[PDB]
Length: 100
Length: 9
Length: 276
Picture 1 (cartoon, chains in turn blue, brown, orange):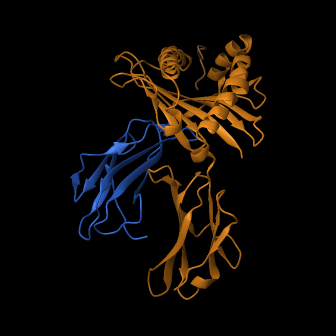
Picture 2 (cartoon, chains in turn yellow, purple, cyan):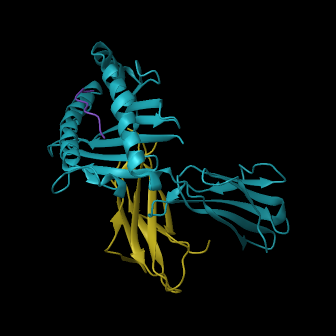
Picture 3 (cartoon, chains in turn purple, red, orange):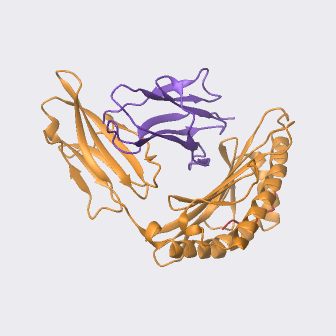
C-alpha cells in the first residue's frame, strides 16, 4: 500500500494588504490515503471558522484539498497551516510567507 | 450526469 | 474549444465499522459542479456551480439514488479486492474511480476514460479503444476476465459515447459565460536580494482559468530546469488558479533572465522581465 505525504502551500487569495480583508488558503495535495486533518493558525492558536473543498484527486490518484478562512492580515499577526497525516510522525506546520 | 455501474470488481 | 467531463469517486472501507465512506465529485474542465458524500447527515447530490442549479428536482433525486447504489456496489468491490489480495479485514482500503469524456471543438468524442485504482495504485483501466482493458497485476486480471466475459466495455462505451458527451454539451450550453471563458493570468516578476552575490526572481501568474499553464524561466533563451523552483498550480478559492516560478540568479545579471507565460486565455505568450 503506497502512502504519499501531503505537499502544503499557504497563501492568500489576493495579494496581502495590511488591514484589507482577504482569504487565507492552505492547499494540501499529492497525499494518500485521503484521511487527513488540517487547521489554520493565527499567532499559534487554531482558527475555528474554516471552510474546505470537496475531496478530489489527480491523474496519479493522489488527493488534494483546499482549506481556507477569511482573515485581515496586519503587520504583526502571524498565520500558519497545521497538517496531520498518517505519513507524518508529528503535525507539520508551515507558516504563511507574506512577501511575494 | 453520472453513469450507473452495477458491475463489481 | 475542447472540453471534458470527469467524475471522481472515492470509497474507503471501514471494516468492523460497517459501511464504506463514498464520495463523488464531478467536474466540467476545471470547474467542480456536483458533489455527493455518503457520510453527510442527509446524503444528496449537491450543486457546486450556479449553472447547474437549473436542473429540475428529478435530476437531483435520481443522481442521489445513483450514488447510494454505487456506494453499495463499491462495498462489494472492496470486499472482493480484499480477497484477491488476501488482506485481513482489519485495515482500511481505498477504491478510486475516474471516468468521463473529452470533446473537441466540433462536439465529437475525442477520448473516453474509465479507470480504477486500489490503495492508490493503478488497478484496471479501459483502453483508448473502449473495447478492451489493461490490468495492472494478476488480481486485476480476475476483474478483466469477468468484465470481458460480460462485455462490460460495451456498457462503458455506450455511456462515454452518448450520455457523457450529451450532458457535457448541455452543461456547456447552460454555463456558456462561465465555462467557455479563458481568464488570462495577471503576471508580474518580483526580485529579492539573497546576498551580495545572488538574488531571487519570482515570476507570478494569478487569477487565471483554466488551470493549465506553462511558466518558464529562460537565460539568453535557454530553459533553466535545474535552477527553477516551481510550485504546483493552486486554487485561489474563487474559481481561478495561481502559480509561480523562481530562479536564483547572480546579482547584476537579472536582465539576462526572462519569464515566459503560456495560457489559453492569452492573445499571445507573454515574455516578462524584471524592471528595477
